[PDB]
Length: 209
Ligand code: NA
Image (tube, rainbow, N blue to C red):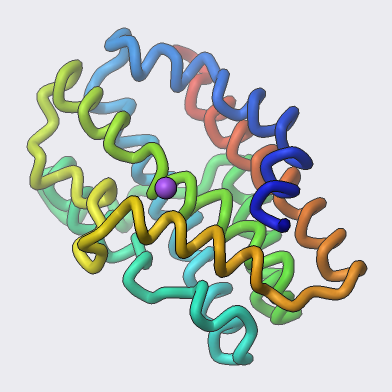
């Protein structure tokens, strides 16, 4: 079904997205808490846009059960950034990198077109990715950079008690979405584009490191 097709269709762009120099250096302990903070600032920008798009598509009544508000990350990230930066200064300072501008532009287009299939593709890449692999990154930020666990709220889903079951039921929801061939093809293409945007985010973050 769709969950399997998504993995197959996106394999090349996904593989490339997981092999950025920025993330390699970050996870091996070669950077610092500052670079982790820059990553989270850029993520706050695109999660904010993503969640506006999710809100629009949810309100239209498309894929409602999938679009669980308990997954919302923007406010959690803001709280992490408050702690990481030590003040609210970051809200006035931070601005989107060129990749994030493109990523946000696309998410805003999806919002305005209330494009359900394309939104689901973005939801998969971010949230199922976060559910699947967030605890590895969190552990590495503590091990390498001494990040306070209270400043890693992004990597914990308070609303979710059974994580393994949740991920299974998430994939099953994907499998059970009613999609025409046009909608399915649109979604699959969008998923590759989403991995690409994310790769480019890392590329920008790694400049001058
Ligand atoms: Na699972």
